[PDB]
Image (cartoon, rainbow over all chains, first blue to last red; front, side, top):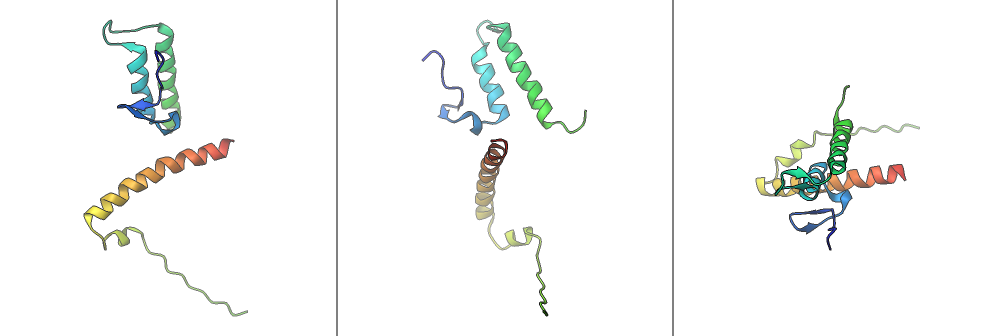
Length: 64
Length: 48
């Protein structure tokens, strides 16, 4: 299928809950960022991955 | 009603001294496997 299963690293089947924040971000760029044109296919997909990285910062930081 | 009791509890790293590099490195990998699995279920079970 043209829309694959998200939770797959190195061709091993996982679930979204059984991924690292790292592995997600890598998987996001693997599908939404194009290597041939060196660009995000749509700007909204950049925003999506961007907001997720913010979320990671939000989760792990201790002070403001 | 005269109920004396003493418990002695010892730092856990003293245990690991009595085994080999191999079994320890085997143990560490499985505890790492516990920790990620445990973290998921707790926060899952908490919010629902």
